[PDB]
Amino acid sequence: QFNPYGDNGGTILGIAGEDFAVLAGDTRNITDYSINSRYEPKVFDCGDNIVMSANGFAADGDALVKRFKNSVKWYHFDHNDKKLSINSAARNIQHLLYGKRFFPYYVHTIIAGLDEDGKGAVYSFDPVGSYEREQCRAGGAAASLIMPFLDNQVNFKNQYEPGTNGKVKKPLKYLSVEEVIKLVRDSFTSATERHIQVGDGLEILIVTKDGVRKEFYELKRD
Amino acid sequence: SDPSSINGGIVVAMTGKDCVAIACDLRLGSQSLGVSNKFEKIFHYGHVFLGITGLATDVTTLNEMFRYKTNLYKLKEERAIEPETFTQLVSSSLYERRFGPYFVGPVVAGINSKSGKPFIAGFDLIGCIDEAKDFIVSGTASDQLFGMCESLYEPNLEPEDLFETISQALLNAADRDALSGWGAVVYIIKKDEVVKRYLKMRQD
Amino acid sequence: GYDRALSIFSPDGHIFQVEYALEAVKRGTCAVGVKGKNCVVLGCERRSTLKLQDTRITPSKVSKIDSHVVLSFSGLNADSRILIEKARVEAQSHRLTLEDPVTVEYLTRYVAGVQQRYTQSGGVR
Amino acid sequence: MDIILGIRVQDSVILASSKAVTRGISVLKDSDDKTRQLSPHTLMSFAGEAGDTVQFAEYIQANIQLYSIREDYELSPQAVSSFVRQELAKSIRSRRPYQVNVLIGGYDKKKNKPELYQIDYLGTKVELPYGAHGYSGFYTFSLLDHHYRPDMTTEEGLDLLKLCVQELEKRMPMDFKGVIVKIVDKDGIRQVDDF
Amino acid sequence: MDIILGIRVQDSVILASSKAVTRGISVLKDSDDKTRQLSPHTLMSFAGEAGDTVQFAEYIQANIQLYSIREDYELSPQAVSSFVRQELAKSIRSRRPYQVNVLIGGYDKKKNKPELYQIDYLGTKVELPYGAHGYSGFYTFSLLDHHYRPDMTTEEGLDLLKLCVQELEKRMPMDFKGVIVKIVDKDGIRQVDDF
Amino acid sequence: TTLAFRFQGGIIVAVDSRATAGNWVASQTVKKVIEINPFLLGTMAGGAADCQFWETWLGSQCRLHELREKERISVAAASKILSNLVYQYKGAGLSMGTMICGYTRKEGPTIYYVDSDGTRLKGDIFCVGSGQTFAYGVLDSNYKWDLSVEDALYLGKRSILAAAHRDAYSGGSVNLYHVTEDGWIYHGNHDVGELFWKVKEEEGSFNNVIG
Amino acid sequence: TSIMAVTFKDGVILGADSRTTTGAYIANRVTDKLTRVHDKIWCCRSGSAADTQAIADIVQYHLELYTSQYGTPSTETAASVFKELCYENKDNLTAGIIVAGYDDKNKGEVYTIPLGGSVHKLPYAIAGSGSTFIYGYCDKNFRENMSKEETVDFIKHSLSQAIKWDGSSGGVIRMVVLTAAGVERLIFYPDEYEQL
Amino acid sequence: TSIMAVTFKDGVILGADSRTTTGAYIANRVTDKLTRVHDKIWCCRSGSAADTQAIADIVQYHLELYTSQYGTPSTETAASVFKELCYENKDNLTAGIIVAGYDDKNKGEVYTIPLGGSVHKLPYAIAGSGSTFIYGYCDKNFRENMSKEETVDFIKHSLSQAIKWDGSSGGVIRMVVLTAAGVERLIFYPDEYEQL
Amino acid sequence: TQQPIVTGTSVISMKYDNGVIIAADNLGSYGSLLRFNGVERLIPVGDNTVVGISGDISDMQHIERLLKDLVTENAYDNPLADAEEALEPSYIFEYLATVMYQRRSKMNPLWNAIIVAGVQSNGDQFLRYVNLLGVTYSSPTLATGFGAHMANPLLRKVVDRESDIPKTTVQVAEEAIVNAMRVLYYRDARSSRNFSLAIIDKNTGLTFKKNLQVENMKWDFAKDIKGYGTQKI
Amino acid sequence: TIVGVKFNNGVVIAADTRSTQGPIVADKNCAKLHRISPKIWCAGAGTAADTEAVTQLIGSNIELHSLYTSREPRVVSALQMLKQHLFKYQGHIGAYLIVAGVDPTGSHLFSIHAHGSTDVGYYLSLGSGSLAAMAVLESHWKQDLTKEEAIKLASDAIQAGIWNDLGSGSNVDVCVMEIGKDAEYLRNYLTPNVREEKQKSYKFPRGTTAVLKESIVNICD
Amino acid sequence: XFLXX
Amino acid sequence: XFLXX
Ligand SMILES: [Cl-]
Ligand SMILES: [Cl-]
Ligand SMILES: [Mg+2]
Ligand SMILES: [Mg+2]
Ligand SMILES: [Mg+2]
Ligand SMILES: [Mg+2]
């Protein structure tokens, strides 16, 4: 019997700073035990300082990104070139995903950018459109490896102030763009080591008020 | 009805500078229902430490079985079994039940009393040996532990530093798994002293 | 389906079909409504050119829409039945979804809405 | 939904309906009224699939109430039962049938007689002196076969009904949290508050 | 078979076990004692598959009684619990396993301490301050987490147990016909007749 | 695990903040209470997407009611819009277990249980979710009508904590709400990480756990 | 079933057996599996009898309506109509059809249409259950621009072997000759072809 | 697989392809499907490689022990031992074996043993997936008391067609000649047999 | 819901300094039966694109007709149909990629794996893959079926990343493709010896080579292999 | 990914060092090269436990046989004992082996499948990355390879697996068995997958982790 | 996958 | 679980 779904592997990672937000994703595309491409980008600039990635089944992922990019275009036409806010984009994507509640998009969606106060924002979606704003989210094949590391290093979970008898927690603070990219690079090198579907290359998209910058780093190709 | 994920639980073992650390959570449940928050998964036969995850009845059975076999070993050999030898005994015993296996993920940890070399090893349910310089992981949050260990770990950590690394690896991994947590225990093992610490972690 | 726009504007900005529908009301028997301090009374004229009538079975001029609301009318008798039926159905439909009987304002607003719909729908007068 | 009983006596119909609403291993409510008044002298108790029961009951209620307003006249229990049966008879061959079993207890004002109708979800109608739906019948029918008389009073009917509830409370596996009892007679519908 | 509870307090172990034996849509019995005395200071309550429960309980009883005669000595609750667990641990990989869950409430005369062991049909043993088998736990564990204290008396333990039975009688779907309560202490095993 | 009970001082609503995908803890920072309007609250249990989508949709339908009728929607009418919606989708595989809690003049404080198989129940106490039984155990054994606003808030919080502990699929943090004649009042986010130990020490409960 | 179409100097020859079976029972032992869709466009039917009969009838209707408007259709056009039905209804059809026609311009042409509904133009085509046993024989023995008598012998010997080994094939060997001369029907009985 | 054994004037010749496949992947393209069970009794293996290897090894053991006690066994005796294993274990075996041996009294003999475990003594035998395509060809072309060169050409042309049509068959054509002279091995490469 | 009847095997391709090479054997398999031997599975669109198709042949012939019709439709009311407004490889691919995903979304897929190889108007090499699921990806080397498992490893030794493309000549690139086709003939049970090869160069344009054969094959070592283990004869 | 290559005066087997549980890499540097006897070495793919267990068992019985017969063991003895064991278990023991070695008879190279079918060849490849490896072997193999050429071809065939197959990765293990010489086991012959320096040290300040209890454990008698 | 207290 | 190149 024809199975309309497939697993294209890979993993994605979104971290939000004070005045910036990064959306990272490995460039490896796979089916079963074969590599399709060592460089197939799945993190996209969608305009209005919104970066988006729909990891999982690449066909459904591409279809969704394509439809959202088109949603941004028609938002400009219908509302006098008004800038689509990250919170408005998030709600719009929920309706795109839930629109196919009974034939779902088999993807974990993450968008990143700046909120209307100019502060870093990351939104994460399940396949059927349940969304939530977070400081931190890993999605895809190696999400289970990366996410608990992010809890520890970004949100300082299970970390207490030395000598305070585990009474005072390590205080929350925003990370610099330099410190965040270090965590992203260490997260993906760790994920590459222990997950077979992750490797080849790492592509990070950084979003500030100035615009969308890109950075690329080599990963292990085994 | 997946034997390995009915009761839940995790074990992690790491090596340091002239020392080894083995740690485990304390949860025993029946799927969603948490039953016991005192169920320790790490045992020891002389100076050799064994941590077992998986189906709880088999964890208890194998502990009793390896106590049985190490006791007879010591009486006949007139010496305590070493980690390298015990690892082979575990592998032998598990594969003996190849087509009716114990649903477990055992982890050996200890220091060879002769050479003084730190030793850790992991097994599948049918006794395949997984030897490692760095760390071994096991249980329902093995994916989480692999991610934590691979990032946090660095070689030749001092016993006091190694404790912090293995503890943070277990705690953060256990918090992302529903069937693990409910308290944790960490064994710091030096050549001729062993410290056992109970960790404070979120009880949900 | 019959699509013809029967209700349309005239050069002077009048919809003659709607205004000729008022002439039909002006022909109809007189109906009066007077509300007191703690009651409303609906008075209705019945023309006396009809003797040998059976007043037991002859449709009454005042109709119950629900147990708490009534509707009297002036104009075409056949037309009134269609509005009364729709109103009675909407009355029960409101109780079913809102778990509360209609307000007199709501029931009126609905009936008025139906009358309006027939003034810019194709194929209907 | 589980236990609904009905006993027609000399001058009235008595409907007893369990108060328990259970979902999984939790009794969510122990005061549920599994009945709707279709007209002043017609009452319908219902049991079956969750959601379908109330949705169906209220749909019938709305239709009978619409008729009452239109004609300024109360439909006979026989007429209402026939309407309900046809709706279920339609339903069973629908895409998703109503999985609802009903008892219709009514007093015919023209005949001056009480009437009890038992209709299952297939649209199977029968007029009975006493009726039950689900596993209740397996105990109550044999009990009523013995103790029931046609010329009994409402008070004798309630004592006969107490004998049924006691037997069910003794031998039924599930806790149905007692019953709400309602009497249909010439004076309309009223609820027994202390049972 | 359904509800078996256990509460270890300061100086005793208290076992509560439901009295209902249900087969199909009939409560066959409402006075069933779901327990066997393994030794003068060890009691085992049991619940699970019909037939297996009593067959297993009596088999264990016979083995512990045989030991008591042979050595002229009572086995510790810990020793008995370990024996029972091994029998179930053998059973689960048999052609037809015993589908029986047990609580072992015992008073260790050497330690002068009460001990409560919870063992499921897989042979999963845990020592607990309070234990339950089946759906009972889903209500009683959270309740005891709140109200239980380790230094409580037998009377405080019985009041704590009444609070559990009341909650189960309120929210449990099935009628389990109350519980038989038994206390294990330094003076042996005795039954509470009025609960 | 979510619960809402009616008492002398109005309605208490308490929910956990955990979302799971199988045995994977996906989030511990989820809003399971949707603020439909100043006098209406909606609880969420089941499919995150189904609850989130349809309860924000319900909020739009409740806004359209007060625009059309120049009057705030009744808790009964609001709950029945949702129950009639999910009933249209009955058998399609919608998984939602919700409670519509609010105050109006004609009704007073009201709670309606609405689930995806079309069940709609008015009641004083409801616990919905995988850890509903654990919440019931503590809530029922401590519930009285004559609880104070302070005691009621705590019992609601303590009942979630009990379930958050025992139920593997419940935890993260407790979100408290108090609904009065003047509308709903938020009573803060309470992390189980700190709350458990604070409650254990002060109350002397949770003796099963190693202190 | 055993069927084939062979192209030669003067045109094309269609050959088929005469056995229709239900399980291991022979429903019809004198079946005509060679059917006329046009004067000098014929087809060979394999698979479900009901399906192949339905398709053939529709094609004949289409080519009759084509002829009324645009004159005589090409053999390629006929094969295209067959393909269109077989391809668009591939889920609900079990039909292996060989289309064979004689034009004056294009001479003898053979198109084979397997289950999928794909079209393959070939110098000769074999199809049906019994074709499997004569792939080796037909490949070795076929030559282009054969004579009428050579092609008749080629088809006769081929279907003789197909019939001998395939239980689903047997009865008489029917053949239809398509040339400029006209349409000739040939029949060959067991007593002749069995002892080849 | 495509395998066959042909009897001629001076004895018998065994022929086989060299293709072992897992699904549509070729595990071994130089397989030896002709195996020695005795000095002048050889067999052709088709079906499960594992099953046929296991059977062949046991038969070789049996005929070695037979020879130690009762001297050289007959080709019929060898076929009987094969049958006994194939028949008694028919539920757990996928083995189509052709047994071919040279006696001085009985000359060249061929026995075929299909899946069932039945024995059939024939003048020549074909077996394996690729045999289906050459039933027509082999029947028409086989003659009794052929020469060595004629039989080699018959097998080569036959397996050439089998290989051409069967995807499960290919590689080199191995052949083993069993005569009074002794045992001769022959190999034929694609570049030769493909363009026959 | 479909099942593929008549099927075509591996399509292999790679980029080089000035353009792209694509190849596919001329076989139409009917399960294990190697039924049809004259099947062209490379279909040129204009003078700047070649679409290589594997999988179901009936669906391949449907895609042929769509591409044929696309050229006709593009020519309508288009004075620059053979110049600036000619069909690009990127236009042809995106059209197919749209159809393939639309068909999978209606649970009635075109049972194919497609590689669109060509050169854009600005001289850039175009090589992208699409299949029955509507999954699309691009790489210096692309292959379908067995090609993905056996050809890609060999072609990636020549062009392992982007920077290797300018360093690879058409002579080296074609040699690697022809070598890969030989390896597939050794090891793919549903492959044939006869194949087609197409080169789209930005300078020399489209070169379509038909009736190529696998040659320089190693079979000699087979004679030395006797038995399955212990056999010495 | 495991392969065997024959050269003039012996045989060489190579294997990758990746062990996987589902999609997760359990062991980054495990040993798939097993010593059946001093001059008979085996490379195993399939169920890790089964390949290790079956190679040890036959290796044990081969040693007892060697002592009994006062002879150096033969590759055909290991081959026969392995295939008859695997066949008996009807493929339930998931061991896919490349058996190679030198003995008094000469140099030998065989492959064994889980169901008990054996194959002979000059070059063989088994495992998930066998197609990637066999592609290289089919491209570059020739008759009359030298020792250094065979090691290069074997390691190149493993590398093809490491890079292209997700099942294979990390390092290349090699064992060279030459006639008249001791078999040289080249553990981690190539290490082309070294982990790059981490961007940051995650060494925690001492006292970061919250502790409830401490206690000295008694390991002594 | 989709998230499911 | 079970480890499986
Ligand atoms: Cl016919
Ligand atoms: Cl073989
Ligand atoms: Mg990797
Ligand atoms: Mg936890
Ligand atoms: Mg929990
Ligand atoms: Mg072939």
Image (spheres, coloured by chain):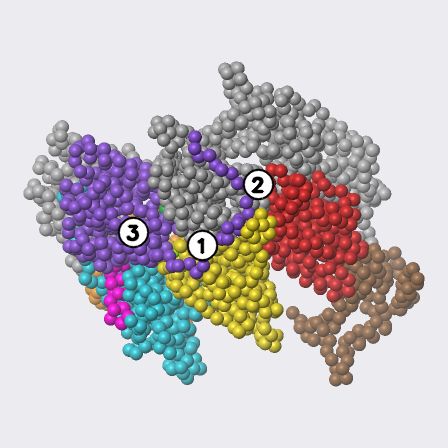
Chain colours: A yellow, C brown, F red, G orange, I cyan, J purple, K blue, L green
Residue for point 41% across, 72% down: I90
Local SS, label 1: helix
The residue sitting at 29% across, 63% down in the picture is I157
The span from disc 2 to disc 1 (Cα, nearest Å) is 30 Å
Q: Nearer the viewer, residue G168 or F208?
A: F208
Q: Along the horizontal axis of the image, is I40 left or right of I233?
A: right
Query: Label 2 is placed on what type of residue?
Result: Gly
Mark 3 vs mark 2, foreground winner is 3
| Percent of width and height locating residue J189 | 27, 53
Q: Chain of mark 2?
A: B
Q: Is residue B10 shown left or right of residue I30?
A: right
The answer to whether one can see residue A107 in this image is: no
Cα separation between marks 1 and 3: 24 Å
* Amino acid type for the residue under numbered disc 3: Asn
Q: Disc 3 on helix, strand or loop? A: strand
> Which residue is label 1 attached to?
B151
- Residue ID at (56%, 43%): J212
Which numbered tag is attached to residue J188? 3
Magenta residues span I168-190
The response on whether ligand 5 sits within 8 Å of label 2 is yes
